[PDB]
Amino acid sequence: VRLPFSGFRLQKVLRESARDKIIFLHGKVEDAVVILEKTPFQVEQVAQLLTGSPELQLQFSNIYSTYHLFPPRQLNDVKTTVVYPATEKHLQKYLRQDLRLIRETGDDYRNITLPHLESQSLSIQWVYNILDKKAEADRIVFENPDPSDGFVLIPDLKWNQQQLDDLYLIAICHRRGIRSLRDLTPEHLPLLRNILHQGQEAILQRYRMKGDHLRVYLHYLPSYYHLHVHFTALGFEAPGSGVERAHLLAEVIENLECDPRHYQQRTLTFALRADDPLLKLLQEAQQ
Amino acid sequence: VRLPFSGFRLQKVLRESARDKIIFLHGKVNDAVVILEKTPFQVEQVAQLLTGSPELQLQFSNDIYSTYHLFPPRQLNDVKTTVVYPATEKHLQKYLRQDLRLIRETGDDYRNITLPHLESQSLSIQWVYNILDKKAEADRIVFENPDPSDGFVLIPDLKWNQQQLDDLYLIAICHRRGIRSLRDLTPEHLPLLRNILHQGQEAILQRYRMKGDHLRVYLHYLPSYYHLHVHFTALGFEAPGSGVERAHLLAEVIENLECDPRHYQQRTLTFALRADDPLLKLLQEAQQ
Ligand SMILES: *S(=O)(=O)c1ccc(COc2cccc3nc(N)nc(N)c23)cc1
């Protein structure tokens, strides 16, 4: 299959991680962002390769010997995400900037964060497309169609589905208007309970993965402002599973049962890119 | 050019890292360990490939977004192959990771199951005492508040080589004895916690010229040793332990104790345990 465009002219390498074996490239085609990621190893096809005669070229020796391996097509998979046409929100996002941590009080959110957010963030159209089945229908793992307490559990774009090691699914709620953790009140408890339980039971049916192998969380300062819950394999150090962003659903539910006004009043901690205008707005508000 | 042995029989997958695109395999030969790692991308070769006609297979398409499966030529298909032959059990022990299971411990679970289990296994924290009474690692103290109750000792963690700030990792050990974990914290510990957070950070700013907003300051629930200690790490340093299933931010810990005094005695804490952990079974059995 052909790319959604014709020809690529690299403009800038937005991000280049040697540790995560990923590259984010901005190119002119019109504007387009192409993400290439080396796929994780599949135990079966590797074990099968080592039992035979592989193509190796020695780098160095010792007991420690290093080689350069050239495996056949099957092992040569690369995850290719194409964003076309890509907006200025996309080009700024993927860029590597130093991060600074900020502690947002209930008043900081009301006065600084919420008005900034309302000034606008991103199009959520792809979310709507999933929810109204205009896209990815074939990939829905489970759906509770209830307009208020309902959701859609779909594997995330970031998971190639070839192995359970990096299992990553999202529960996207059917109800519109819940931007983040900050909009949550006790009226959202039946929705959240539905996600926690029905989302895990769906993973158990589909992937035979017990709930104690799952890390179920929300992100504070999410990438998109339509409530979504992450379901990640525990052995997977999922970028974003870190304490400065992740909030366990079970704990979110429990806090809400304890303190109804919790997420509206309490101070939330998150990181922001040094170049983020919101970071300055909060910094200035705090001094 | 070839292999140091003849034939491979995979017995056990020692370690996996789907984020690092690496695999650790123990296999029987002629005992050996083969490490396979996907090689990083080369901007040039990739840019050159996208300007032409690549072999792509669509996974799906949604709005402006679309995912594919790419099969590049030989030049992009390199895999780093480290071979350890012959292999011994201590290497098999340093290279094998245990399967983890998550558990949600209620206040009552801790009181009835966790605490009695902890008390059963007589664990020595003599090395901690040695630091505190300066019998060991005196030369490493970055900062010390000597107050017997509200005081602490700030020491760089031994894994941090101190040659760069990128992986800055310090630990504060409190002078006061008897605070095993997060579960022992009450509002009486607020002056100590406030000193650890504010003094610890001020010391890091003076010593390392690292502003507080570049620091992730946390506690571990189910710590490796049961004498209260807080971690001070560089924010850009993403290395497990900073994950939500274990880390608890000191600032948040303080705020919780200001709101709910009885918080850490009553509330349900979530953490992971190694599948072979006797405590994991004890909690599982208690819960059903
Ligand atoms: S990026 O290219 O890394 C990138 C951009 C946007 C998003 C938001 O997520 C999706 C966009 C479109 C479809 C989609 N479908 C599923 N199943 N899951 C997600 N997460 C997305 C992600 C990555």
Image: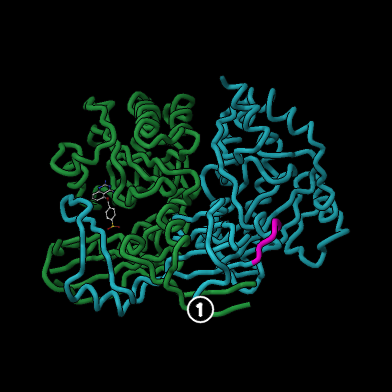
Chain colours: A green, B cyan
Q: Quadrant of residue B227?
A: top right
In magenta, the rendered stretch is B86-90
- Relative to A180, residue B56 above or below: below
Category of crowding for the residue at label 1, using alpha-carbon neighbours closer than 10 angstroms: few (below 14), some (14–19), many (at least 20):
some
Q: Choose between B88 and B257: the one closer to the eye.
A: B88
Res B259 visible: no
Q: Position of B68 compared to B138: left or right?
A: left
- Relative to A217, residue B207 above or below: below
Task: Tell me if residue B89 is in the magenta stretch.
Answer: yes
Helix, strand or loop status at disc 1: strand
Q: Choose between B4 and B51: the one closer to the eye.
A: B4
Q: Magenta-highlighted stretch: main secondary structure?
A: loop
For disc 1, the marked residue is A58
Residue B104 in percent (x, y) is at 55, 31
Residue B192 in percent (x, y) is at 71, 45
Q: Quadrant of residue A86?
A: bottom left
- Relative to A253, residue A12 above or below: below
Res B19 visible: yes
Residue B223 in percent (x, y) is at 67, 44
Q: Chain of mark 1?
A: A
Question: Which residue ends up furthest to the top in the rendered image?
Answer: B288
Would you say the beta carbon of the disc 1 residue lies within 8 angstroms of ligand 1?
no
Q: Amino acid at mark 1?
A: Leu
Position of the N terminus of chain A by quadrant: bottom left
Task: Tell me if residue A54 is in the magenta stretch.
Answer: no
Q: Position of B196 compared to B145: left or right?
A: left
Q: Choose between A284 and B155: the one closer to the eye.
A: B155
Residue B77 in percent (x, y) is at 36, 70
Q: Position of B131 compared to B212: left or right?
A: right
Q: Residue at x 54, y 69 (%)?
A: B82
Q: Residue at x 17, y 75 (%)?
A: B52
